Length: 100
Figure 1 (cartoon, rainbow, N blue to C red):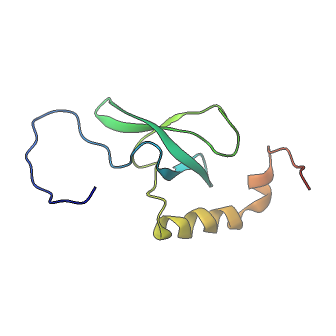
Figure 2: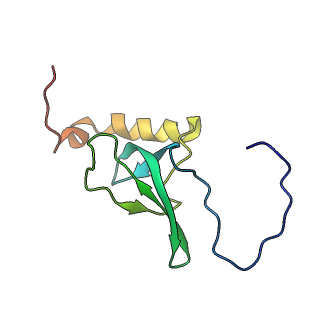
């Protein structure tokens, strides 16, 4: 969407930043995990987004706020990577190795 940014809005719930289908980075602990915006809900005066952990299908999916999601941009990547590399073992723990 490319166009001018002009238009007032009433006193209604806030608008989200990320869109469904767009690849984003969710925060599921001391490490970032690749995910995509499944849905976008708004309540309790906060905007959330149904994340879908790519790692495993329907992996106990959970709802996350707008601060727990990243724009999956270079900047954001700089971290997601720093962590994924900072702690390998931990990241591996839990997962079922294989496919060697």
